[PDB]
Image (cartoon, coloured by chain):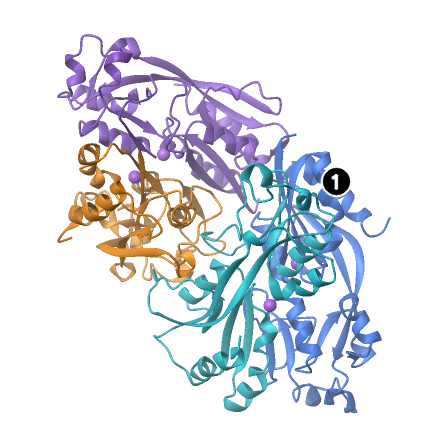
Chain colours: A blue, B purple, C orange, D cyan
């Protein structure tokens, strides 16, 4: 109904290309131009709170208890603690022991900058770390043997199969619920349509 | 509510400060941060069409009756053809004659800086012209004796009283309806509230 | 024909008015003195939609094809209305304090989103306006705290309508004249010579 | 203890990986190689939130105090999927034509002096993404026409997944290393010496 602009935020763990089917359909449904922006952890939620994002696709988080924010579970994602095959972490009797983990470099994706608070990986103080902005940069660092870190399984599935990466220990494997969140204090055609279409991209 | 952002566009003829009462009230009604942006003629409407403005306050225009756009008349504004007291245009028998107007410099508000003629005296081809972006710059140019142009009466009322400007000829005085316009394809709390409050600013 | 000078919002357009009559005699050139905000001024120069830009010294243009010359220095003062509570603050410039009070921004290239001067924190209230005058009126009405060009508020501070929040935040900015070297028309060349003369000793 | 290098989106972060082990031996410094887009990279430097910036050329100072050095040249190519109708176009770069086809933009963290890597026109359909990878995937999927860094699509062009729209639009950009002189830590100094060595021959 004349040109419109909707802004979807996909957190770093969420593949942006999964939302590409929406683009053509949104151009036919309305005259709506899509913006699918990437943010990291709390940065995704912050965008929603500050009213700078129509819909957020992100891991379930403590922010969700907000009264004017609706939310719905989309799918589950698996996180695996990986390292390059030749990394010494593999020869460790107790790779997840606090005494062992400090010996080896962790790799973190920043949310705004170097931020100690993280839940995916418990980086310890005095432990070496590398910090990057993108999930791809983190992958390349891991492929190059530069540290040990958690990754979304889809992004490293081929890597593990083809022996470029190796799961450090299955004990650390975690499941994260990926949720769709939005604010009820505003509504439009395009936003409503997306809220209905996005779940269809995944389960049903 | 938590933070929200609304964008009101006020066309150059419309004093932005008239919307200042909204600011404090909008901070209490919701957590909404206001942006009152100035545009010139068609630029104001273009923002509305492109979905880059929640509400537009602008002169009534050829854009109107557009199917997705609601509108409401707010008030009438008077436009006066003025020049500095010492300007030779005052000594002219026929100041508004095509033969006369070409002799003297017109002043236009634009961004494009090429095509002025829209709704009023306008600028004749081959006529000397100065182009400025703001209504204030146009006022100063007129005060400095540099040309002849239309101005919104409120902005030059004191100038005419105190003999800094002088109405060239009353024949050219025109009335413009200032309307509030928005798009129906979207709605939220703040937007709805403003659509109700803005007319109240101009009751009297 | 047609010359376009772009004066950034901080730069008073009327300072260029002396050029108008002279340019009409020197050449048959019709002048446009267009106002833009921050990056919008430079963008016009890059896109070849402005012959000369008068603007604060700033990043970009890929460091290709842009000549520049310093015209004068401008002082920027952090001001607020006399009765604004920011004045009673022990630490008015502390991040903990600044968040309490509304900032006021002039939107850049004339749009809401492009606003990255500085001084605005998350969770901080803000108002965004298009013009430096609108920002002045907002400040006069007590609606926030913001930086202003000293010349535009000098009388305001004298006559007690505004008050400098803290001198520590005062900054000096070089106002430069910039153009592209890939063209040198008659009118353009003449203006490049005349414009510095408008500001001599300043 | 903590050094922050900012690499603009056009710059491959992994090119700086050799530094990591050496920096751990040289000093006890934990490295952050952060990605930003266009002006967002510079803004970090101005706000003192980045020790070193690797980014497309600016060379211009509002914030002042900035030293810079050229590292290497990068080529940008206007590409689209092989089956995109832009290829059948007589005049693919004509303003009349470009509006017909969707542009793809990487969003910026700052005052958008660079907004269009090539040029995005009003009324023109657009998709906006945050990352250069997302933009690549969009292009691979046939969803628009946009500029890309040649190294990132060299294999794509070879293996017929992408195709250069027109060579006329190809542009060369200097990638520079920039920093502020008002500080000179051990690690920062060492990196400023090592980083140029990573791009000998380039
Ligand atoms: Na992304
Ligand atoms: Na105004
Ligand atoms: Na001006
Ligand atoms: Na990167």
Q: Residue furthest right?
A: A204
State the SS at label 1: helix
Give the labeled residue for mark 1: A25
Residue in front for this viewpoint, C28 or D45: C28
Spot occupied by residue D43 in the image (x, y as percentages of width and height): 44, 61
Q: Quadrant of residue C143?
A: top left
Reply above or below: A167 against B99: below
Give left or right: position of A166 versus C146: right
Q: Residue furthest front?
A: D90
Give left or right: position of A176 versus D77: right
Reply above or below: C141 against A173: above
Spot occupied by residue C168 in the image (x, y as percentages of width and height): 27, 62
Residue A177 visible, this angle: yes
Reply above or below: B203 against C1: above
Residue in front for this viewpoint, A183 or A147: A147
Spot occupied by residue A110 in the image (x, y as percentages of width and height): 59, 68
Q: Tag count in the figure?
A: 1
Residue at the image position 34 percent from the left and 50 percent from the top: C146
Residue A188 visible, this angle: no
Residue at the image position 21 percent from the left and 46 percent from the top: C195
Q: Quadrant of ligand 3?
A: top left
Q: Residues within 10 Å of mark 1 (few under 14, many from 20)?
A: some
Quadrant in which the N terminus of chain A appears = top right
Give left or right: position of D184 versus C73: right
> For disc 1, does the CB lie below 8 Å from ligand 1?
no
Give left or right: position of D11 versus D51: right
Spot occupied by residue B58 in the image (x, y as percentages of width and height): 44, 25
Residue at the image position 79 percent from the left and 80 percent from the top: A166
Reply above or below: B14 against B28: above
Residue at mark 1: chain: A
């Amino acid at each position: 109904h004349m040109e419109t602009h909707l802004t979807i935020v996909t957190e770093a763990l969420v593949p942006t290309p999964a939302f590409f089917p929406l683009i053509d359909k949104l151009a036919a449904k309305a005259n709506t131009q899509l913006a699918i922006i990437t943010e990291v952890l709390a940065g995704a939620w912050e965008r929603l709170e500050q009213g700078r994002a129509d819909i957020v696709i992100a891991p379930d988080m403590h922010f969700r208890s907000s009264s004017e924010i609706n939310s719905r579970k989309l799918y589950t994602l698996m996180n695996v603690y990986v390292a390059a095959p030749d990394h010494p972490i593999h020869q460790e009797p107790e790779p997840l022991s606090e005494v062992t983990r400090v010996k080896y470099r962790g790799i973190a994706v920043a949310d705004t900058a170097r931020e100690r608070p993280v839940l995916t990986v418990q980086l310890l103080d005095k432990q070496p770390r590398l910090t990057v902005s993108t999930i791809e940069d983190k992958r390349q660092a891991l492929l190059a043997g530069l540290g040990v870190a958690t990754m979304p399984y889809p992004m490293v599935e081929k890597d593990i199969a083809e022996g470029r990466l190796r799961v450090v220990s299955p004990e650390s494997t975690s499941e994260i619920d990926i949720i769709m969140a939005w604010r009820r204090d505003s509504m439009g055609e395009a936003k409503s349509w997306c809220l209905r279409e996005i779940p269809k991209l995944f389960n049903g």
